[PDB]
Length: 351
Ligand SMILES: O=c1ccn([C@@H]2O[C@H](COP(=O)(O)OP(=O)(O)O)[C@@H](O)[C@H]2O)c(=O)[nH]1
Ligand SMILES: [Ca+2]
Image 1 (cartoon, rainbow, N blue to C red):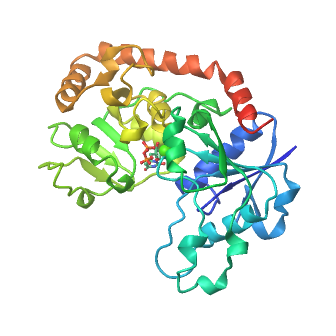
Image 2: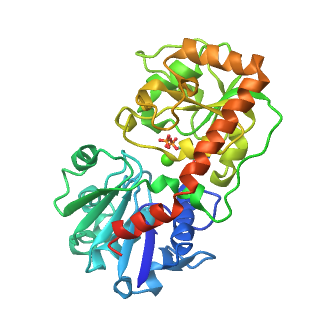
Image 3: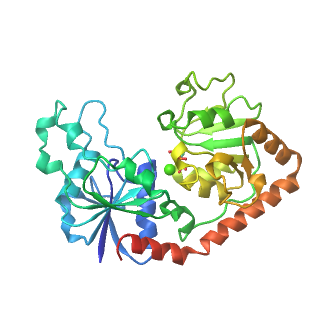
């Protein structure tokens, strides 16, 4: 049983980039459950083998981390093209890890054939014909199926909480008490404005000391539907393996998601935040049944409640430590189910 895992549209080298980090984390967690796996990328490296130096069909299972397939600028993006060429040569079922609703599996050919550099490729070379099984991070498979209604060879769908890999790593460790320098913090990208309403609601015009770290920038928030006056402080992006440490700088950290994530996806940030020294405050709409933590104090319905809850935490260190103890306890309860999670992953990839 030999497994190959690849990222469909981003180069993989180390933890200096997010897509690379995620692919390496998956490689590691799969390896930690006793499976033989190789990461195949553009070139050889610490964690990778090159597409040009291995036969994709020497592997019994091909796992693909979702990615965008859009082309921008000049030169052809080999990260996308070489990955799809590799996939097109595989003669068995492909397991597509669908962790981001905006990144459903799609054929690159249609987006290539009209490019000025289209002559460098052929349809037969890029057209992926193997059957594809989508492993959905969201429990709602209808949302996952709708996202792939445009691809005929995607014939199977199964839900699996992929994102829990963060808490199941052998070297996992909870963040320790940290000196606070922020009231609220949130790390992420602008996500093409797919979450602008929630970002403005909970992070803007709060009167609190809020930091928004990641690829997002103040100048991106200009939708007339969600006006604001005072924005949070935007700082640069940081390595994925430093996120919980970063969240720990704040008293509380925000949990929001895209509309289609509500009561559907449990994202990586839920675990990165739960494991941090920051109290997790969740948008009521994201988890209406309070399935993450059965304690209403961790949920906020709007800007007003977020402000109230944050001030309550600032005023009472005991309340803050009490809630942190609760979220760390619930986190450990899920970590205690690692065996079940591993077996479910194996089942998802037909092992
Ligand atoms: O500076 C940063 C900001 C974010 N992240 C990662 O990016 C994720 C957020 O992704 P996104 O903005 O797409 O939001 P999501 O949809 O995951 O909530 C976080 O959980 C981190 O894993 C990171 O590595 N560095
Ligand atoms: Ca994510």
